[PDB]
Length: 104
Image (cartoon, rainbow, N blue to C red):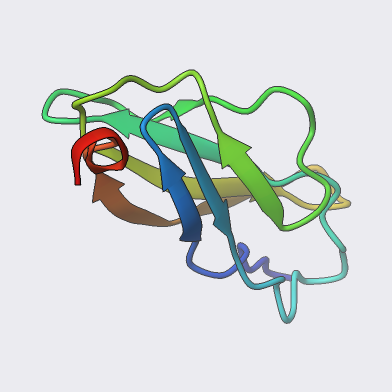
């Protein structure tokens, strides 16, 4: 009885202070359905993955806020399963400077 984390997160929109990304729902998950889709953000060029979200991401469509301008931020999606286990982090999403939206 193994577990499979959600699909690789891909940002649909990336604001100077709010990066929106969604992913693909799991396909196996042992015998669970997952009841939360957390996501860690990396504050480049000196981050360390930190679950920004804190409002329970039930739907595979969340927005990572609390970011900063002129700073590349990467975002992976970590999520547990109905059993409580913790499905590894979903391959972080491309690091967005989160500034071009205010310049180009």
